[PDB]
Image: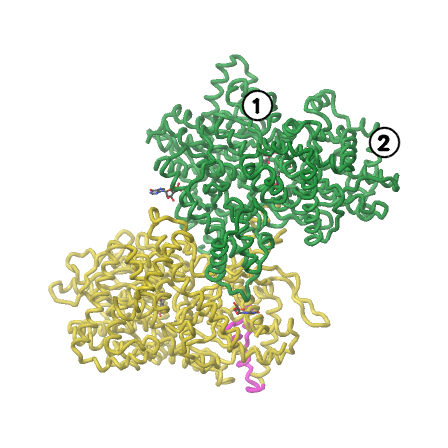
Chain colours: A yellow, B green
Amino acid sequence: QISVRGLAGVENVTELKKNFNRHLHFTLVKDRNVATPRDYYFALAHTVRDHLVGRWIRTQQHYYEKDPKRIYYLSLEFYMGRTLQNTMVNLALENACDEATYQLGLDMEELEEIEEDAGLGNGGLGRLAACFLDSMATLGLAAYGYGIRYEFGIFNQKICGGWQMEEADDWLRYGNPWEKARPEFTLPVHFYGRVEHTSQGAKWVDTQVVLAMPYDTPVPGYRNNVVNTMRLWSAKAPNDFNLGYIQAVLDRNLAENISRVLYPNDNFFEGKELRLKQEYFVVAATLQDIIRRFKSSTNFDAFPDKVAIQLNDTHPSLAIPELMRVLVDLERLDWDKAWEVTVKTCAYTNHTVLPEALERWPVHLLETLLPRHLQIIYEINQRFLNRVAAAFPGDVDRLRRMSLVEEGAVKRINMAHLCIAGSHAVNGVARIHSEILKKTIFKDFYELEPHKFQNKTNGITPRRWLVLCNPGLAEIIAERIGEEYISDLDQLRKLLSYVDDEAFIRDVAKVKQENKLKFAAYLEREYKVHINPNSLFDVQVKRIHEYKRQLLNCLHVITLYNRIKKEPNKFVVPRTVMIGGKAAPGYHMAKMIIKLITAIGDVVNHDPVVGDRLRVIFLENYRVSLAEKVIPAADLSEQISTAGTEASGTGNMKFMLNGALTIGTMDGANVEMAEEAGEENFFIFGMRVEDVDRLDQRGYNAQEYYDRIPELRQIIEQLSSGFFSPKQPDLFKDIVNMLMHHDRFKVFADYEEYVKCQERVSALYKNPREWTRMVIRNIATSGKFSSDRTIAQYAREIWGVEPSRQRLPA
Amino acid sequence: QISVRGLAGVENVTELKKNFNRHLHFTLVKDRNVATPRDYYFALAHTVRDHLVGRWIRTQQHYYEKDPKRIYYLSLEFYMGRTLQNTMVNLALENACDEATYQLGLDMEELEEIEEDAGLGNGGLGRLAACFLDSMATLGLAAYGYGIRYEFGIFNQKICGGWQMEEADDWLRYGNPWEKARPEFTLPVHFYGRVEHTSQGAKWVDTQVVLAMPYDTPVPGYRNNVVNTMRLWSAKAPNDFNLGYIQAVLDRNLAENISRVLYPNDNFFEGKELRLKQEYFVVAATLQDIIRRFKSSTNFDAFPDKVAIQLNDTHPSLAIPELMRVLVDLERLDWDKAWEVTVKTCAYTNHTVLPEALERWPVHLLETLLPRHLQIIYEINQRFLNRVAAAFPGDVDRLRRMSLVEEGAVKRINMAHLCIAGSHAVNGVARIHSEILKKTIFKDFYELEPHKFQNKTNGITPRRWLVLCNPGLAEIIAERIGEEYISDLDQLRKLLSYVDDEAFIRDVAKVKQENKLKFAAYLEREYKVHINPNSLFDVQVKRIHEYKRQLLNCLHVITLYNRIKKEPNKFVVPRTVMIGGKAAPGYHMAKMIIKLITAIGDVVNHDPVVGDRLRVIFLENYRVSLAEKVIPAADLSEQISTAGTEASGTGNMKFMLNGALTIGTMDGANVEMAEEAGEENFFIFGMRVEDVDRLDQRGYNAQEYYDRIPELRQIIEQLSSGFFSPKQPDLFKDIVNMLMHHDRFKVFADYEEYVKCQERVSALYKNPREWTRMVIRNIATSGKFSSDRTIAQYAREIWGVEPSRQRLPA
Ligand SMILES: O=C(/C=C/c1ccc(O)cc1)O[C@@H]1O[C@H](CO)[C@@H](O)[C@H](O)[C@H]1O
Ligand SMILES: O=C(/C=C/c1ccc(O)cc1)O[C@@H]1O[C@H](CO)[C@@H](O)[C@H](O)[C@H]1O
Ligand SMILES: O=c1[nH]cnc2c1ncn2[C@@H]1O[C@H](COP(=O)(O)O)[C@@H](O)[C@H]1O
Ligand SMILES: O=c1[nH]cnc2c1ncn2[C@@H]1O[C@H](COP(=O)(O)O)[C@@H](O)[C@H]1O
Ligand SMILES: *Cc1c(COP(=O)(O)O)cnc(C)c1O
Ligand SMILES: *Cc1c(COP(=O)(O)O)cnc(C)c1O
């Protein structure tokens, strides 16, 4: 079909068909007479999986023989999405499989849609981990992702009567052909117990044991024959567990609950015992694996030369005291030596400055669950504070501020402070965020140890986020500049030479139109919703949070509706406004916001005077596989967080790479995207961080904006009086009261500039040539936002390893 | 090697090696550098499994096309043991696989020992179901075994300080290569709710749903290319189940507990709610499958022409009211028609007359869990009792005796009475048992419907129980009479021609000696216990129950020990006395019996005057795979139940086929074994059923035997005074008190005749030629006890189908 999808050679196609039929018969135990599309999906998956194993075995053997420094990426979340297409892309098998299936009378795209997402994450942090695995493999790093195999990932979202309902994500129901269980490599993890002090030191005794059983999933690099491993741990009861008889067997479930379900909070901290168990479970099992591999390469001086441990936020922070526990209690290293090793091995990435997201564990929980770790944390704290006191003598308030132990009604351990003390590098995830860390929440720590603090601006993988999801765009680029850009995204800068090329302009606009048609068709088929494919597709997809200001978008939509009703016969640029994302089940306001969006839709979409000029659609069950569909279809990307709140964003980058223009605040990576593209090619509006600070100083009074802006007052009166909820007039009272009196995120303060900026978007959309020229200037300057660039920086500046695009032999 | 194991052709061996290597690489994702014996076992298993699938697909397609009457064998237990060797035997692959593995540098016997038993049963009833599946496939019947896929089978038994400890049987830890999950064929099962009566009849509403997910396991016939299915159901929560959020997901465990664990009672009734859920779960899922297959072959007149349902005891008895519920409530048949269909479809096998084993469910449990079924049971009862009243007018006590509903403090449903009312055939499992049913517990029912009552004497499969476990014996037989006997066991009668053949006599004795050496070696290797391989191997293996009288064996052992101590310099025939079996976890007396056996061992095995003349060994963790080892090594088979208590026995048959002589009472199938072999070739002793009855009439007084038998008094004084428990003198007080005052099984009444009979065993063992001639007379007359004979009788006399030894094309 298209060149970037590879060759469909006769011998390859013949072999794929043979192996497909072999798996249908022997693996699935089906005859073609009763096989369903799902059976055909599994036959194809097993066929493609076979192509990984030689490379996987050879890669891991290569690491054993060459003994490179090993990189361990520890995360509680890996938001992997679907694996089939990504595997074909990275092995150059897509066209061959397409031809093979076509010859068997099957449509490969239909088969691809059967696969469940591996939804083992909430949003950006989980998806970053997934992009990072892809980039580490593509850059030939000896890297391992370590996490938890959740039986249930992020819930499936259903909308019922305009409200979010949650359904369990039983993603393993039909099996997972990508993973390989390794029950032979099961390891013990200890909980509870008590500490005995002997002549030979501390002993942690009388513990309860849970077993950690690993499942390995292959992670292929882009056409370099490197296949790395993601190892996810599953909890199992020991066989003597509780061992009337029947009840003891049933009670095995209690241990096995550790790996049952992903906590569904994005950017929020819930201090539950089960979450702490999950965090220790991952850490304890992973560290045993790390030490085993090191010993099989007694001298731990070389440990940091052979091992790097990257902490994805504070969630695996217990790695720091666990490494200390192993080195001191089990290996009998002196404390100072063990600490030197630990600091040189560990590095910490921070993802948010919102205080409610920070992990502060009550001491009483740690005392009960992990009594030896608590002792170690207290010793770390005492030695760290002794350093602070020597550097800043007499500064008693600094000692209180920097302590790992927080005083109050309930004493807590600040896990971020632990991570900073115990890591040689601390990074934020975009330039503005990294600067905020040094100036605000971690200022004291930066003053003590400035060398620790780095920036590593986030990125996205151009394999999933261009080649896989938008083959039409990938092909028209490849036609002009070849294929090298797929693993060297800075080559997109070559496209600036084509900004005045009439053929390239029409082809870029053509690809977008095709994607919009395809998406419009998907919506009609799966959700029986009709949209106008000639309208501007205005898209905000991300988790529902007050800081992300879906509410600001809502105010704009109502503004547009009100303007139409006031002047029904005036031309306006038609829009389809699409908002999607999941709310955390316990987050009342986020659930109310979803209801408001659907309620706006109910009014706008059925008003005959509006016609097809404005449609408001809530995209149900936003997830990686839906992102792959909607992002290539978008014209306008909404990135409208209050300045200083979105650490980076990564959705923003996906939109830029796929030919959408951005309306956004100077927040997170938006700042760098605008810098790369030129501010003239971005729709920037609203308060800067400095402006937010100035408002906080004099005090935010929402009433002032209400009093001064008639169009805004109308909207608030409509919300309050029941215009969007005729049967329940007070339905949205909580939203109104929040906006008027308790709005941490200053929605009204950016309303006027946002609406004006949106007017400029509409004006440009009326000129398709100039819209498309601006799009080209965005795509062409997207290169910095490849996760390959991000990972190269982690490798050189934190881990001390050199990337490689060299191919292993097949 | 040996002829009965088949051919090792060059092309076959080459292909097996190729596929073994393919599975090691692609399926297991291992290189040979790090592969362990367990990896090699799995590679071999997958290789052998591949040879089943073509035959499995072709067999099931054949049934779809030809549409024979289908036989559904419903059991809560299938005691399958290991599958690898059995599969090779039935496919004629054993020698080829042996050669293939040998050429790869592997020992196939070593690999076989890695496989876990599928221990999804307790003992005889579960093992009968397994033998029956093998025989149904060998006889070309369109038969399906339906049961539950327990996550944990019968517990692993450990002996600690002489006491039984139970450990969970986590048999699925490393995976099960034999089964194929069929999540696509998942069906709903309903519980709780209430009944609404409408114009259109009864409706069962407001139910809780559990999903039944089937796993299919292939069941190969002996060299006929027939592969039938065992379908086992696993419980799954629906995805909206309970749907704070985390707890709702965790609570899915409650539904999934239905299939978690096998209830470990042999011959005993525990009326727990979870057991009732298991029973309904199997029935409801299975019946949906049955009806679906029937409809895809509205007219239910033909249903009994196309379907037979065999109830393995009363455990799946709810099939009767469930079939009625479906036909009346869902298909809208009139009651009388539905009842005609039900009776003609169902048949019931009874396995015990012990009252404590009979299922009598409290009405209150059924009312809550299964309210519609209870209504149906009451209607069945009323109509049945109307028939009784018409046949026996005025016989009011007969109405009370025959009722399905039992009166008392707690009203109960007698499930056996339900099964008799609702089945066209009721059978016992040996001639004496079937006669007992008609004369005692089911006398009233026999008087009403004599035509219903049949006998089907049990049997064992000669594939597992001769060819697989005792290839040496199978070969020496085959050398004389060829191989046809393996599927036509009556051909063993030809061996009577060889009873005076010196070569055959030495070869039979040689095979036994080899098996004894091998077993002695196994015991030393795995349990560091040494035994004298020239001693008489005296074996009692079966579940520990008072009715089986392991205690009578114990008294004999102590008698032998006491006789040695009294006359240390007198010659006696050396014995190794081996007793093994599991006790139900809640059965105190059975646990005490195990402790007594180990305590006797502690004394006897360390007394220097005894030397190697007497050893007492408790065989730990008795299970199908251990039976395969110990039975071929046995000289004497102990089958010593109180007359009238062991419905059949099947261990007895295994011993007879493998060249052990039997010491036993005239109980169960022992009666028929003696009839076949000649009473002169069996060591029969003790009370007959008629003698037990006479003692019950005047009253059993154990004191009389104590007063009259000095050797018995000595033993009781030894037990009471602490001779076998010096540190805890009163340890065995409960056993003594039971024997003296509350012994339902009359241990003392058979003591004198048992000891005298044992003296005759020893006398014969001193003459190896005459011992072996008697063995030949037993092996030669074993033919009746093939499960092929049993199944042919069920087929012709109950199910209305003709067996076939015709081969399907490969
Ligand atoms: O996604 C998260 C936070 C996740 C989480 C927190 C606490 C839990 O308990 C669970 C998950 O932050 C995001 O991490 C992304 C990648 O750097 C950034 O691009 C986003 O700006 C940031 O909000
Ligand atoms: O094995 C059982 C009974 C099992 C059971 C009962 C109640 C539960 O709740 C669970 C299991 O009976 C055995 O069934 C065997 C085959 O016919 C017979 O050979 C034995 O004589 C008989 O004792
Ligand atoms: O002791 C060993 N001998 C030979 N190869 C080994 C050994 N340990 C690890 N390897 C190789 O390294 C791979 C990865 O092992 P891991 O890193 O311990 O998971 C294995 O699959 C082998 O190919
Ligand atoms: O509708 C049908 N068309 C063709 N073959 C069928 C159909 N239903 C069942 N079969 C065949 O019968 C086999 C057994 O199906 P089952 O008896 O319903 O489990 C299937 O695997 C097919 O080979
Ligand atoms: C990229 C992505 C995110 C992160 O989007 P932001 O706008 O940066 O919050 C969340 N969820 C999914 C499914 C994604 O693909
Ligand atoms: C045959 C068998 C039984 C039944 O033995 P009986 O002596 O008839 O009770 C029990 N358990 C196992 C493992 C068997 O193989």
Gap between marks 1 and 2 measured at Cα: 42 Å
User: Is residue A391 shown in magenta?
Assistant: yes
Residue A715 pos. (x, y %): 24, 64
Front disc: 1 or 2:
2
Looking at the rendering, the stretch of residues picked out in magenta corresponds to: A390-419
**Residue count near mark 1 (Cα–Cα under 10 Å), binned few <14, some 14–19, many ≥20:** many
Mark 1 vs mark 2: which is more N-terminal?
Answer: 1
Residue visible at 71% across and 52% down? B524
Residue B18 pos. (x, y %): 47, 59
Q: Tag 2's secondary structure?
A: helix
Q: Nearer the viewer, residue A124 or A589?
A: A124
Q: Amino acid at mark 2?
A: Pro
**Quarter of the render that holds ligand 4:** top left
Q: Nearer the viewer, residue A754 or A489?
A: A489
Q: Is residue A670 left or right of residue A533?
A: right
Quadrant into which the C terminus of chain B falls: top left
Mark yes or no: residue B186 visible: yes
Residue visible at 37% across and 36% down? B66
**Residue count near mark 2 (Cα–Cα under 10 Å), binned few <14, some 14–19, many ≥20:** few
**Placement of B767 over or under B698, stated as above or below:** below
| Residue receiving disc 1 | B442
Judging from the image, mark 1 belongs to the subunit labelled B
Q: Which of the numbered marks, if any, corresponds to residue B710?
A: 2
